[PDB]
Length: 345
Ligand SMILES: N[C@@H](Cc1ccccc1)C(=O)O
Image (cartoon, rainbow, N blue to C red; front, top):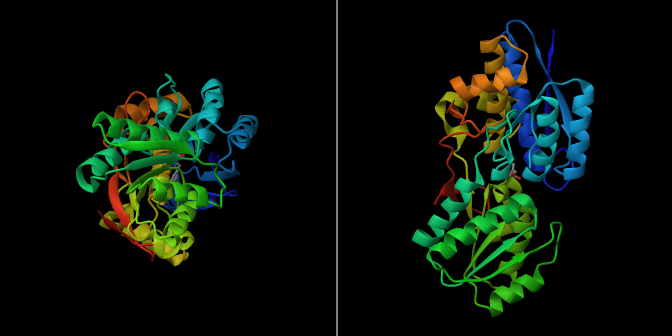
């Protein structure tokens, strides 16, 4: 019979663009696996849920998935939506592989039914710090975040890395997501002579901050995590995007092995360049690999199978640890441009 797979992330709300990547990836993976035969003849059927990357809606989606009888979830997208959902999946015996959530705590609580194909901010944070310390070498640093699990997690991790090396972090502060007016913060960066800012959060805020910064003449170097590194960033920020630093996964679209899938997305006129197309595609491949190899429909048998034997995916040969995290997932540093391109820093 058909095998239902829930796919969960933002299809509404302020970061729906990251969701667009996720769904585009999941859909192409499901199509490709079904075109190749399915799972010994059984077709994968994607069942899509919008959690708006909102913790309360995520919980409602998780409860709906349980009620719907679905046993496998590729989701959720954001850390603060994925973690409360994971509590329900774990309790109910449902497999959950997140292609998006990077915050460490998800997989540090002993859970057995949870995995990711996303990286960890316990790696992303230190990488930013190292680059800041060793290459940027700033004089006066401010660290800003959006008071949310992902962004504040990362802002804390970078502060910790920088303060370990006695760097001059002048202040640490939160802003409210959705904020369109950064004139107060920007005046502070100017008056306090801040030449470097790290912002833990997502592109809508980062873009507005960059545009407003350059409009008053601030020359401050900004940096953020992969959450800011979107085609939207440069549209929102304008020429102010130029020079922004971002940590991001490898450019899987440039791997020659993916040229066929790149072409598939291109024939649909979908953008293939975002890392999360591939990271989601790889979660679907992972689940499919487990289903094919085990012949089991048990979530825990599928998770045991991936942790023992791995999967070959569009983001490379995958190996997971006993907590459900990928070994060897690294983030690189990139320099953004007004036209939305980016170069290795
Ligand atoms: N990694 C982010 C979500 C994210 C998904 C896709 C791209 C960028 C960011 C988090 O844990 O919330």
